[PDB]
Amino acid sequence: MLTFALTIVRAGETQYNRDKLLQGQGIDTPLSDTGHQQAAAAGRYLKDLHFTNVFVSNLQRAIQTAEIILGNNLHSSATEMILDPLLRERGFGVAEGRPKEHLKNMANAAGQSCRDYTPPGGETLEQVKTRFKMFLKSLFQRMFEEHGSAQPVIAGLADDGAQNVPVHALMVSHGAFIRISVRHLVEDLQCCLPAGLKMNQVFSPCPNTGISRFIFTIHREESVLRATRIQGVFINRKDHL
């Protein structure tokens, strides 16, 4: 109707990951050398895939990660890299630039758990979730426009779940945004899970340039595009590291 693969990759490391500082949207700096190497390893890993569509956070570390992946790709040089602010990392407001532990301290000082707490000038979970839902609606519209009309095999390889799926989007984003996105796919939209992936495993944090994959089936429910099936394939893969 339209079936398409979505590969999701977290940005590479900046200078600030090493120090375990909260980056969010307000720390917008380039990849470290490690970051470059992570992105290059991810690019070699995915080099045999044709990405028909590429969507990227407009934060620099995400842009560069995507550039390096595409620069390593054997098939996707004609693909325009779409910059989408909807893919930006969760904003952590005044907490940005502080070590990650400080966020815990602020939460505790406000009598709230970390899941409940939003620092001044940051986004709530609901706000980020809203950005992913908007991205998704926009994703479905763009994918059906270019590609639409009226069980995954998991071998431990770069093309798992997508060996014979020609329509393939790449999404390059950030750790907290990706975590929230996966949660929406898994919890809200109740996507199928493969091979021993369950609730417990699916919610682990994605490492820098960690790679996840879902297969979407979509159609027109009389003028409204909806997913008739979302199939998880793999989450947070880092073999290339």
Image (cartoon, rainbow, N blue to C red):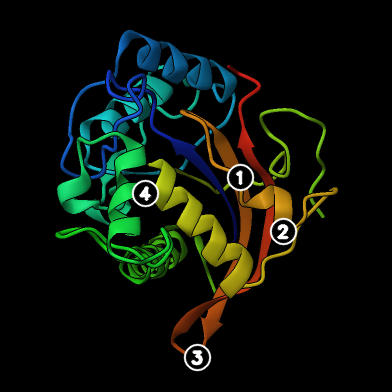
Secondary structure beneath label 3 = loop
User: What quarter of the picture does the N terminus occupy?
Assistant: bottom right
In the rendered structure, which amino acid carries the disc numbered 1? Ser
Q: Badge 3 is on which residue?
A: 222
| Residue at point 49%, 51% (across, down) | 179
Name the residue located 53 percent from the left edge and 78 percent from the top edge.
226
Give the camera-side residue of 122 and 61.
Answer: 122
Q: Secondary structure at mark 2?
A: helix
Q: Earlier in the sequence, mark 1 or mark 4?
A: 4
Q: Is residue 97 left or right of residue 157?
A: left
The label on residue 199 is 2
Tell me the quadrant of the picture where the C terminus can be found: top right
**Do the residues under discs 2 and 1 have CB atoms within 8 angstroms?**
no
**Mark number, residue 104:** 4
Report, in whole angstroms, how far the alpha carbon at label 4 lies from the one at label 2.
24 Å
Residue 17: x, y in percent?
35, 25
